[PDB]
Image (cartoon, rainbow over all chains, first blue to last red):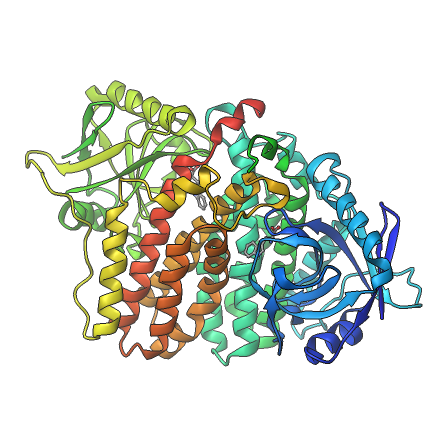
Length: 309
Length: 309
Ligand SMILES: N[C@@H](Cc1c[nH]c2ccccc12)C(=O)O
Ligand SMILES: N[C@@H](Cc1c[nH]c2ccccc12)C(=O)O
């Protein structure tokens, strides 16, 4: 049993964990991930779905034993995905992609859940109020949320950079990053956007950050942990999947993203172990995925009033 | 000397190619790429910048000898890009990323160039009328534009799928794909989009397709051609970068993309040679990059009127 606290709406629900179908994932949440906090997003495509990022690389490569069509899942079902989400269905879904269930919100708490889901939708559609979520073991108080830090690494250069990136990831974990807020308000040093408007810039912002985190960066992580591709080859293929997106994004306004990427690309040829490679890339990957949660939050979805079925 | 003809606005300019700075590039265009047609897009972020797609894998990995800041290039400058573009500056740019020049539209055609530039803008911004560009060696008239096909490959199953995919890419080269048009009109069988709107779906359609093409797929082509990564490893790493994006887009409405990806992923472990790997990923790659051009064309950029600096 776990509790899920949405702070701003002031709603807490309780969910039963199950080791029956996906024991490795249940065990991962129960033992390795809890307790944590995150920025709570609402799905913009999939339907009445809530997901939030968990700052732990294991979610990228841990396999499920059992997946089901998520639209057929009962409301209240809790999932874990390799996009590093914990997810909860609270109403109908259109996205029929397989998902890995690990439990469900107790029957007594479903109304609370749907109510909370609507509060989360309202925040992303209208108010832009960042909604903090706290997840912890049932009946275990926490007054200490801090992002995990990968074990230190025998390399002053790598470790220093890892710490810097992770620190920054924590700093803006539930606090809006200024470089994201600024772009949405048009405060953009480079004036990016054709013909004096920055709407397109926001679409490209929203568009490039997301795959860079979950696809390129997390892909490298997945490959690194689940295959025996050599360190030399990991090092070689990395600039190819991560340089251009970050560079273009740097111009649009993500100076910190692009700065971090340059320092990583700069250190990368000289790392000596797979452990060093992984901490370096993991730190950037989490930073990238963190930014996506804020784009999900801040992007003007409101325009969809003019795009109803 | 080449000729760039924009069909709809009835404008044809002449450009001098130069071997002074990027000989390998100028050569490739001159001997390898001409003549061709394409869909003319206009940059939505970079400024007064025209770019279109060229159906040749060599642009992905052929290296520039020289690059300069594009904001400082004279109006009229022609560039080739590893994004598979021929690009022309016709006014101020804000994107200061380096680009490889290969020539210039002649001085007496600059006015005609800026007319072509503004007309392409009108098509992206307001009209959504597809503009066809035709590019030729000066002198030699051209009647048939067919997409380049990779040389037949000693593997019938691979070769068949390669043919089917290339055929399809050719079919909707300058004629809009129904799957893209239908989505932008809300004709989406899965009703993807939270709370009965499909605007968010259009943002994600736009955002996911582009990196899948230029970053994941094209990245694998470049890795295959510019490094000696083993075939065994090329096959191992491929699904990690291309499955998840394609599956989600399939759900959102791109049935053909997801079907072509699944087929590629089924044949991929059976591939026997690098040449077989290359042709298979290359065909899927171009198709993906082809879809990007239509997203760039059809996405409702006009919303930018509420986002002026
Ligand atoms: N369903 C998420 C987005 C999403 C789900 N799976 C994906 C895979 C790739 C990219 C985006 C996604 C939303 O609507 O907010
Ligand atoms: N210039 C393109 C966008 C672009 C340029 N370079 C990129 C690299 C990655 C992604 C997008 C881009 C436009 O504004 O239309």
